[PDB]
Image (cartoon, rainbow, N blue to C red; front, side, top):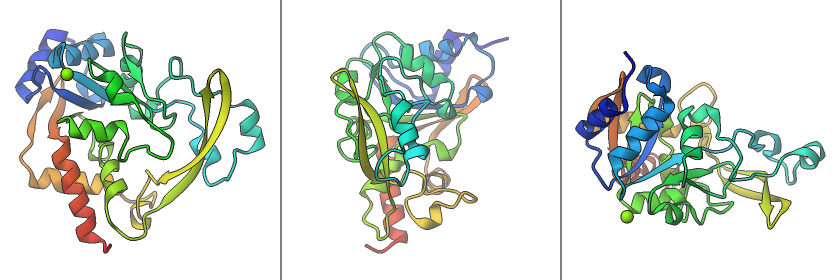
Amino acid sequence: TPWSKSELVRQLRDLGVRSGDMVMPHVSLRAVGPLADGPQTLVDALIEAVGPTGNILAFVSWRDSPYEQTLGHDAPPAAIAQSWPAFDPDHAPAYPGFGAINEFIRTYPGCRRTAHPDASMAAIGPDAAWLVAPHEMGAAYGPRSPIARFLAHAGKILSIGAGPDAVTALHYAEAVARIEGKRRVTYSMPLLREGKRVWVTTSDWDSNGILDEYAAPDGPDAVERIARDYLARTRVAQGPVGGAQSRLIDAADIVSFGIEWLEARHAA
Ligand SMILES: [Mg+2]
């Protein structure tokens, strides 16, 4: 028997989602189980749970981000520059690796989408426009980004069967932590500026390992190691949503914990 919108809303309220909350979900649909009407069921359940004053913020990115193709170059390679589509926020699909639910959030009526092609965020609710803008190249997850405003606005992270590596908000801790040797990357994105395609080159913190020891492809990154420590040490509301084991995390709390975790382990 597939889960119905009404059942998921009950489970979400028991977990601690309240009317008016600001919530950022990380979802594994395989762990939730079958849904009355597919993934849209869970989207409808989330929106009903935060109510007409609440807000949802999602990390959706872009299916065709040319990050790896432009990484480390001072300009896009000519093959890429000539034919790559410009990022069109109204039509560019979400990145499927971060979850199949994100394409449903993105196309929900009234959803606003941030301008950063690789770090694109989508938001639904009365405060959506204030959350999604500005989102400039060179400020993907740090101060001035949608993540910073989420943290200041009492955001909650809702992890529905997702692992500890999935907590995007911890990239804010990497950005602001006073530690030595932080990795940076250079890359290029094709934006749409008043109708025409423009390539912008920028640098930003490496989001695949903020220090060399976290950037190995074999081992865990800093996000995973912080989240695991936090969950072993902290009382966090835990409970099912659908068939998936879920958690509701205070975003400002886990991010503060991560800044201190990084700074305790590395000199300034
Ligand atoms: Mg409000």
